Length: 313
Ligand SMILES: NC(=O)c1ccc[n+]([C@@H]2O[C@H](COP(=O)([O-])OP(=O)(O)OC[C@H]3O[C@@H](n4cnc5c(N)ncnc54)[C@H](OP(=O)(O)O)[C@@H]3O)[C@@H](O)[C@H]2O)c1
Ligand SMILES: O=C(O)COc1cc(F)ccc1C(=O)NCc1cccc([N+](=O)[O-])c1
Image 1 (cartoon, rainbow, N blue to C red):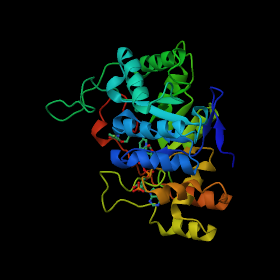
Image 2: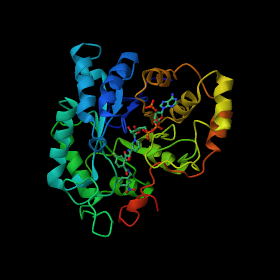
Image 3: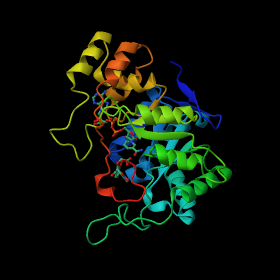
Image 4: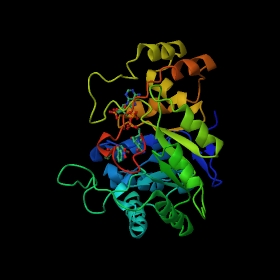
């Protein structure tokens, strides 16, 4: 298992990265420092996570310390929904760059296909509680992303939470200049994504799996929800291989040619989660894990279901 995957922009992307959604601002600097110290070279970020400044402190310190060189890091961020208009994309990218202490991003994603009304609120609401859409579509937002490549702000551009038809819309865009390098989607044994993964891979788009552990710290968790880390069937595979359940859950997407971005702020788990390059799941293990699919989503976007571009109908 090589550590990097070749993207369709000619650059290589580390297949294991550190997630940062929900990482508290007072803990994420040390989390990223530890991650870099123990071998991580890819950090997944977003403006909406409200902690990019603190992620950036860690990156800058490790560059200053010469623990790593900038060209060895692969830093990803995402354009939030309230910045889909053409005139807002560059400034949104530049705010993320400033916060992360970077001159360029390795990859910048459209975070969700849904555009929302610009303003201070990340979820602008009407008086009845619906999110207020923007009238800017995915194709014009994509053209604005292409400009960022042509200005040197980002090395690669991609998409996130785009369904099959939305990916195809991008690929079929009149005058398309750069194909998306990545589609970052939720993926784990309860949401195995065979159809969307095969489509993206067949077009040369690399898939990144988010919430690979089932996001046990998601803010909307309910007790009746299934739990990957506690599933006896997955624990049994881990025991057979003398690895933790989390390690199995991270290795699983790796063997599907996916990138995977487990989140932790716990030093011992950050290190544990990286120790996944030294064992192999069998084909039978892989098919068994795939069999657990139930189309269960951490990020279901249930408050966004009437948006013309809601992705999960
Ligand atoms: N593009 C998108 O729309 C989108 C959506 C969701 C997520 N993402 C990205 O994907 C990343 C990962 O997804 P996620 O944050 O939803 O959840 P996740 O990575 O599936 O799970 C994170 C949770 O698992 C715990 N954990 C981590 N390693 C563990 C281990 N070895 N043993 C036991 N528990 C462990 C963490 O606890 P501690 O931190 O307390 O250790 C945290 O509670 C995000 O942080 C974000 O970067 C992107
Ligand atoms: O979107 C992520 O990366 C994780 O989830 C969130 C993180 C945040 F910091 C804030 C909000 C979310 C969240 O609600 N994310 C879910 C979401 C967002 C936008 C649109 C949709 N949609 O289905 O169209 C869904």
